[PDB]
Amino acid sequence: AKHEQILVLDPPTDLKFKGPFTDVVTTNLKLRNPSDRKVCFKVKTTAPRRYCVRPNSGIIDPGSTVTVSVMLQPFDYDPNEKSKHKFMVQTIFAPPNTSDMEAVWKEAKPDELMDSKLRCVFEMPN
Ligand SMILES: [Cl-]
Ligand SMILES: [Cl-]
Ligand SMILES: [Cl-]
Image 1: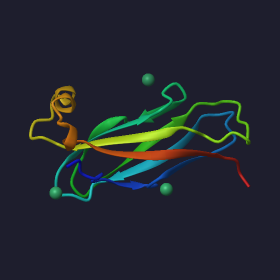
Image 2: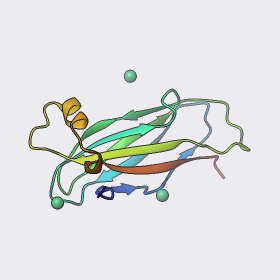
Image 3: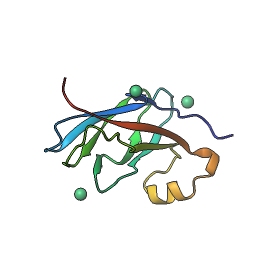
Image 4: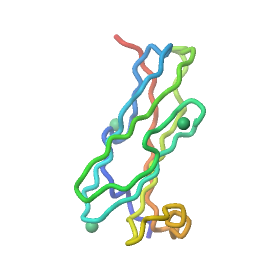
């Protein structure tokens, strides 16, 4: 059975980016690990040329939290266009050996992976 996402995300669903978008706009995403085990994570967007994410991967200690910076590139914003961009978080419980994360993610069984999706929202100041 594919488990639910073990991490607690703040914000849990909607990532908001406040304009104006003539500059780089950054929004934070906190990943909290409420379990007693290390959790490896990977964070991606559906538009890699417009977003950067730092860090895009790592391991979270039990009970700890990491802040992920999502950077939106400047663009010409039209208020009558909603953002169709999604943000994927993929997590897996860390195996004992994590010195080779490429091998860890590749050996991962399908049900060992946990996934969360966040929607993006563009907004201007009031
Ligand atoms: Cl939310
Ligand atoms: Cl646990
Ligand atoms: Cl880079």
